[PDB]
Length: 51
Length: 49
Image (cartoon, rainbow over all chains, first blue to last red; front, side, top):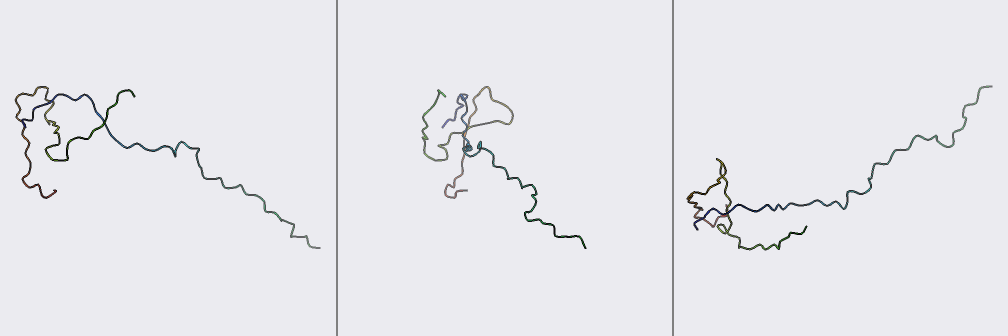
């Protein structure tokens, strides 16, 4: 138990978690565009001129 | 990668079985000159804190 000074280390291992990327890199999934306003069907001339 | 190594977690979990790594707040060593290193620990080993 003299606890002498040992030599300098050769290198460094570093352990850390890696993320999973099987999900991302996929084609994007955007929010679907709301439709442009379309005229309602069944619009008729309700007003007829008097006389 | 060509270099590799077989892992082997040797050594039982114990206090002074851990290797000790030393820094110094005043610099790098660059020369170990007759530095008597001595590691002390508490007498009570029964409470975990």
